[PDB]
Length: 117
Ligand SMILES: C[C@H](N)c1ccc(Cl)cc1
Image (cartoon, rainbow, N blue to C red; front, side, top):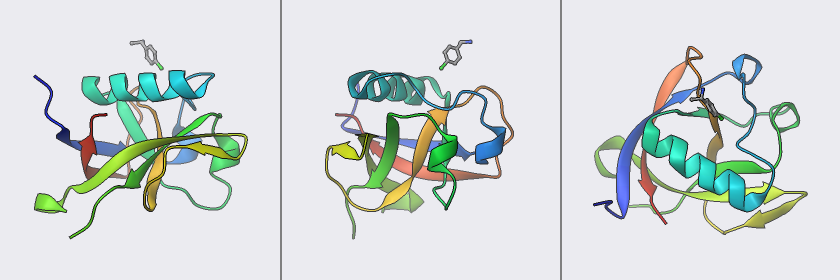
């Protein structure tokens, strides 16, 4: 059975390498697909810097810090989607935007403890 949180190590991708620049076409779909790719080990993370979001496809799926005081290095996170400037969920600081991973070479791995909600 699925625990409330799962430890994952996500490949961190540079935005210009990403081949599939979002998870879908509605908030509900992107959240659903992100969660599936996270379970399958086929989800990457792009760190948000100036110029990143316009190079990715909306709706966006962010991982945001959900909790403080981070077990074994994995930051606790939850998913929040964004479309047209409106966010679906509320949480803490953004760690990055999730994208499909289809074999791109990462620059780093990001350890997270993901809330499965
Ligand atoms: C497994 C298949 N080649 C696939 C990769 C990425 C996405 Cl987003 C959907 C399907």
